[PDB]
Amino acid sequence: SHMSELSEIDSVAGVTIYSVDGEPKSFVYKAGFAIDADGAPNAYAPNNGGTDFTANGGDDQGGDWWGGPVDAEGYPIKQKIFDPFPGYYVSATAHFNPAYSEDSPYRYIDSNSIPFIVLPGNHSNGAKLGDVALVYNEKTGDNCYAIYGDVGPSSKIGQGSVRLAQALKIDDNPKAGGTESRIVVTLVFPGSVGKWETPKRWFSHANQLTKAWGGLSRLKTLSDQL
């Protein structure tokens, strides 16, 4: 394809975020890819039983716990017999399905099964949780549609779900996976969805926007500009 016209709109951690001039509206950045296991129902459990170390969700003994919802005494909610991993903690994502209660793993986006990206807090650049994106790994040639599913630290950029890592052929392990190399190009369509909907529906919408925008071929050429 031809090169795209790019206009800087933001910068986080040395990564420039560009509006892609034209329609449909989109922005793009090239960054590393840290693993966000948030929302996976096996991410966190007592005594380091999860796929991540427990302390990466905070203090599970009544202290500051950010991994997910807590009970009235500040301890993480444990999954029930009707939840995917009974006795593990409920891990939360910023994006959620309103059909389920705050204490339910089903309210959150399962990182193991759903391709999702993280955007830095205070750096959404017009995107709303549930909006779609096209994600491309320039070193493997792999790609995947994804939703904006979680919010990261305001000072960090380039992170996504276990399943997105799998789709991109990046090591998906929450404890040692991901990459610091700036090899992932993320094209976000702000204003595209802005709510929870079934993955079949948002994936189809991502496909329609990507076709209108010029397809992976255009993003491949654009990656050489970043």
Image (cartoon, grey):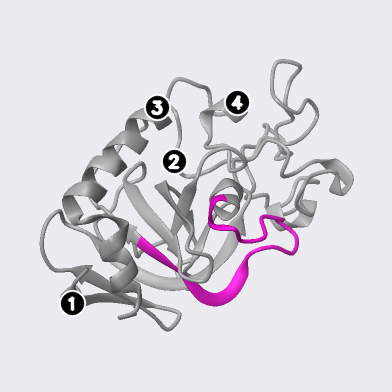
Lower position in the chain sequence, tag 1 or tag 4: 1
Q: How many marks?
A: 4
In percent of the image, x 46 and y 73: which residue is there?
31
Give x and y (percent) for residue 97: 44, 29
**Bounds of the magenta span?**
167-186
Residue placed furthest toward the right: 47
- Specify the amino acid type for callout 3: Thr
Task: Measure how far apart labels 3 and 2 are at the Cα level.
Answer: 13 Å
Query: Residue 115 location, x and y as percent?
Result: 50, 45
Q: Under tag 1, what secondary structure?
A: strand
Residue topped by disc 1: 7
Q: Which residue is mark 4?
A: 104
Where residue 67 appears, as percent x and y from the top left, is 64, 47
- 104 displayed left or right of 197: right
Q: Quadrant of the N terminus?
A: bottom left
Q: Which mark is residue 95?
A: 2
Three-letter code, disc 2: His
Q: Quadrant of residue 226?
A: bottom left
Three-letter code for the amino acid on which mark 1 is drawn: Ser
* Residue at (66% x, 55% y) in the render: 172
Name the residue carrying label 3.
198
| Element assignment for label 3 | loop
Q: Could you tell which of marks 4 and 2 lies nearer the N-terminus? A: 2
Residue sticking out furthest to the bottom: 14
Q: Tell me the crowding category of disc 1: few under 14, some 14 to 19, or many 20 or more residues within 10 angstroms, Cα based.
A: some
